[PDB]
Image (cartoon, coloured by chain):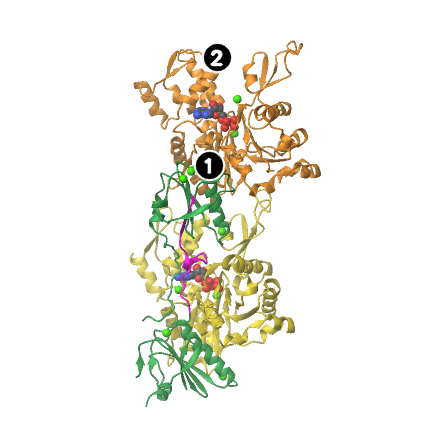
Chain colours: A yellow, B green, C orange
């Protein structure tokens, strides 16, 4: 039989089959409920919406993130999501397919135990494994020891791992990621005249981010170049044939990753958090971490972000360090890729947690499993 | 010990003919080396890093795992192989390279064109919809047509059709939307201002848009 | 050995359209009129009858006071409506309604009490096995092939804009205009009187209806068309009366339907159908207006004038922003679109679960009709 892989990301769910080179189903991890309740009567709407359909019907719905900031906080909505994944997105019955889930770093034991319980008792999965997103990313890079920068939709993590084990004393969480960047790009665009009020116009801004934005190597010189010339401007055509000119926004938006002060956060940029994490590791392994720095997640896709991170990091590290930043072209979904690879492997099958074991020892069996 | 990586298993080599589109695991008792070609695939990369962890786990847990990218070999390592031997070829991949999109049926999607005609059956419930060839050449005007594009659904209403035919066309297009996750918007084209509809047949049956940066699951060969 | 056949009855402001489900056209079409004798002196001998319906009432005026039960699409007299329905069932359709499920149609914004009374009458007076009430414009849109759009229904005595999303009407945005085909006939009658001709007898009014339905058209640009008709004979046309006399009509041909766009012609202080279509669209959620402009369907007998679609597109494009895609749909079977949709709806096999059974009525009273 073929196994299933599901990365429950903060803002998008990435699901697919073990063995494929990419997640077949990718959709927003969002659930919306009617906001005026009188629309489930006279206008005949269903009680909840998932993913694309919910976001489309934003406006008559209150949208909530079951996994806002990476940790699941609503098991009814998470159930709606997973049910959608299995039955509607993948079109399979989960009782016939083992299911690998991913969890955020610093996931509570109770959270993972409830995840386990729900999979087995509500979806009758034959077997399941929960892995840590950054670890799957690390393995996918071809490495077993390194430090991962995982920037996604609602939360960003620094995670150091030595010989396949995460170091929770030094794991770093930062509540800034792609979604706040989209919001900020919207704000600074609206500060130039452009307005985005229709649901369509609000999704347009996410598109502009993903297609036109890039990370400035030196913010000062790049800001100056955009102020004194038009070399850096670039144009984006709306549906309605009107065209928009965007200039410094292209690199002011992602700079927030390095200067959270842009959105009113008192916090540290991704370079600083990488540094503080590495220094919080064993003193003997910091060299190995500096030399193996893997980037994963959707928010590490801006062009020229590898360069900037190396710059700010080398400015932080001791002068004699050999520093290398790893940004493989498949990093947007490396997590999912790892699951797909790992679930297909022959060595892994011994690690699968069967329903028999769940019946025998309760939900705590999930803690007693190595990668 | 030396092993090329194949699928997930390890094939033992003792000839040190290093290749550029693969990954090799070298076994020294207290330090495990994994060497990742500059032109291999992900599965080959990640199977190395997985196997090394299974090996260090068997070994009580006192071995050190040394990942090394091609061209960057450390002297410590290079002094175990050599008394530069790097070939160009590969051992195959295990992944299936898919391309993806807004619906999970993507990488295999062929756009469909169906015809609906009440001339052959009596009553709506008796009517059926028949796939015809995805081409303008398959369009009559006595009846109606529906194009399933995956992303979207187009409807073409002939001027010489009847109400029952357009009702089936709508039914069928809304059914397509229902049975496929995410929204697949229905767009009705009347015969006459049908430029985009014919334009879609002109994009042919193997045309699907995805954005979503596509990637290839094998060495470059 | 067989199954059962269902009835479709559109209770129009001026005409009753009734027939069987599955047929492409209503077998019975007759005036929605009830006539009762001038004074009791007439029905003494019996002699005369208590009341007359439809064509016979039109045939016997002058001894009958004529009334419209459904003068404005909303039923206002249940005795006269009962006579109408009775005539429909027994005289025109020649069926026993205890033997057929009966789908009736109602105007937009029908009061709930009104629809409950319709229900009570059908079940308690005609023992209908089943009945369903549908909204006229919704059947019209459905016949156009759609479940979302905005319908312009111009009939005999009333005109409506109805926006519909996913098959449900939006009553906050429903627009009513108490002007329609009959007011156009009356006005045409007057303006022909102003040319020499004189129409005042009822037979002369039927002739005027024929002249309207056969010769009138909607000018694309009223100023220009008036000028063309005033400086040449291109727009003139001749109509032969029954006695073989020919008459010639010129600007009347388009001044008559022009009233739809300029109600001031009949002394109404109100806005033309283009304006109200716009006002309705504006009363809807901003997210759907794009769809409404793209799906603007016309139904009813008074949307039959030629070139009314082009004019509608012009005036709506002038009202709406420059970048909107406006599309005006004028299905050829729109004179009966309502009814035909109903026919198809009752035909449907999926439909039958929705029929309201007599059992459910006896058990739950008339408010079940809302479900
Ligand atoms: N080329 C790109 N540049 C910048 N951001 C991108 C790009 N492609 C996708 N993204 C963003 O990445 C974010 C999602 O990352 P993801 O891996 O889904 O994290 P998570 O799964 O934790 O939500 C979204 O905000 C999306 O806009
Ligand atoms: N071809 C036509 N041109 C102009 N008016 C027409 C035409 N056909 C029908 N009508 C008018 O349609 C009106 C009735 O429309 P209909 O939808 O049957 O209204 P209702 O539902 O109010 O009975 C009549 O006034 C008739 O004169
Ligand atoms: Ca993620
Ligand atoms: Ca060890
Ligand atoms: Ca290879
Ligand atoms: Ca036909
Ligand atoms: Ca045909
Ligand atoms: Ca759908
Ligand atoms: Ca691929
Ligand atoms: Ca009507
Ligand atoms: Ca008649």
Point out the image quarter for the C terminus of chain B: bottom left
The residue carrying pointer 1 sits among few (fewer than 14), some (14 to 19) or many (20 or more) residues within 10 Å by Cα, namely many
In reply to whether residue B102 is colored magenta, the answer given is: yes
Q: Residue C55, position in %: x, y?
A: 54, 19
Label of residue B163 in the image: 1
Q: Which residues are magenta?
A: B95-115
What kind of element bears circle 2?
Answer: loop
Q: Is residue A66 above or below residue C37?
A: below
Apparent side of residue A200 relative to residue A114 in the rendered image (left or right): left
- Magenta stretch, main secondary structure class: loop
Q: Is residue A25 above or below residue B218?
A: above
Could you tell me if residue A277 is visible in this image?
yes
Q: Any magenta on residue C69?
A: no
Q: Estimate how packed mark 2 is, as few (under 14), some (14 to 19) or many (20 or more) residues with alpha carbons within 10 Å.
A: few
Task: Please state, as top left, top right, bottom left or bottom right, where the N terminus of chain B lies in the image.
Answer: bottom left
The disc label shown at residue C200, or none: 2
Q: Which mark is residue B203?
A: none
Q: Nearer the viewer, residue C331 or C191?
A: C331
Most extreme residue toward the front, as rendered? C1
Outermost bottom residue: B83
Q: Chain of mark 1?
A: B
User: Foreground mark, 2 or 1?
Assistant: 1
């Amino acid at each position: 039989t073929t196994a299933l892989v599901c990365d429950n990301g903060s803002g998008l769910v990435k699901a697919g089959f073990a063995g494929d080179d990419a997640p077949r189903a990718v959709f927003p991890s969002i659930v919306g409920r009617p906001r005026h309740q009188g629309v489930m009567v006279g206008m005949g709407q269903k009680d909840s919406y998932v993913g694309d359909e919910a976001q489309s019907k934003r406006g008559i719905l209150t949208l909530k993130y079951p996994i806002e900031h990476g940790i699941i906080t609503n098991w009814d909505d998470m159930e709606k999501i997973w049910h959608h994944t299995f039955y509607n997105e993948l079109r399979v019955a989960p009782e016939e397919h083992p299911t690998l889930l991913t969890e955020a770093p610093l996931n509570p034991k109770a959270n993972r135990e409830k995840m386990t319980q729900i999979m087995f008792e509500t979806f009758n999965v034959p077997a399941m494994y929960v892995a840590i997103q950054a670890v799957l990313s690390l393995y996918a890079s071809g490495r077993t020891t390194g430090i991962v920068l995982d920037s996604g939709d609602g939360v960003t993590h620094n995670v150091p791992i030595y010989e396949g084990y995460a170091l929770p004393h030094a794991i770093m969480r930062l509540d800034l990621a792609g979604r706040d960047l989209t919001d900020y790009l919207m704000k600074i665009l609206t500060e130039r005249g452009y307005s985005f009020v229709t649901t369509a116009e609000r999704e347009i801004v996410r598109d502009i981010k993903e297609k036109l934005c890039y990370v400035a190597l030196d913010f000062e010189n790049e800001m100056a170049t955009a102020a004194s010339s038009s070399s850096l401007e670039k144009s984006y055509e709306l549906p309605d044939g009107q065209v928009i000119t965007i200039g410094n926004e292209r690199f002011r938006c992602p700079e927030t990753l390095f200067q959270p002060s842009f959105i009113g956060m008192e916090s540290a940029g991704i370079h600083e958090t990488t540094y503080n994490s590495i220094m919080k590791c064993d003193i003997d392994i910091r060299k190995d971490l500096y030399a193996n720095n893997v980037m994963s997640g959707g928010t590490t896709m801006y062009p020229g972000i590898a360069d900037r991170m190396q710059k700010e990091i080398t400015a932080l590290a001791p002068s004699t360090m050999k520093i290398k930043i790893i940004a493989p072209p498949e990093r947007k979904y490396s997590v999912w890729i790892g699951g797909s690879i790992l679930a297909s492997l022959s060595t892994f099958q011994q690690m699968w947690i069967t329903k028999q074991e769940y019946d025998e020892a309760g939900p705590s069996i999930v803690h007693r499993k190595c990668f | 010990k030396l092993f090329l990586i194949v699928k997930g298993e390890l094939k033992e080599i003792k000839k040190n003919i290093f290749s550029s589109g693969d990954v090799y695991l070298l076994d020294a008792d207290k330090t495990i080396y994994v060497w990742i070609g500059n032109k291999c695939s992900v599965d080959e990369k990640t199977t190395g890093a997985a196997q090394a962890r299974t090996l260090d786990q068997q070994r009580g847990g006192a071995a050190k795992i040394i990942t090394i990218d091609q061209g960057f070999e450390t002297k410590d390592f290079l002094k175990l192989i050599a008394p530069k031997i790097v070939e160009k070829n590969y051992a195959k991949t295990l992944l299936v390279d898919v391309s993806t999109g807004d619906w999970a049926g993507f990488n295999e999607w062929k756009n469909i064109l169906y015809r609906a005609s009440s001339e052959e059956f009596d009553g709506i419930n008796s009517m059926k919809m028949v796939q015809v060839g995805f081409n303008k050449s398959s369009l009559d005007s006595e009846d109606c047509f529906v194009a399933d594009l995956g992303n979207k659904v187009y409807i073409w209403q002939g001027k010489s059709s009847t109400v029952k035919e357009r009702v089936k066309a709508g039914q069928w297009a809304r059914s397509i939307d229902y049975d496929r996750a995410g929204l697949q918007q229905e767009t009705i084209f009347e015969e006459g201002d049908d430029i985009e509809f014919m334009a879609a047949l002109d994009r042919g049956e193997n045309y699907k848009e995805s954005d979503a940066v596509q990637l290839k699951a094998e060495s470059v060969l």
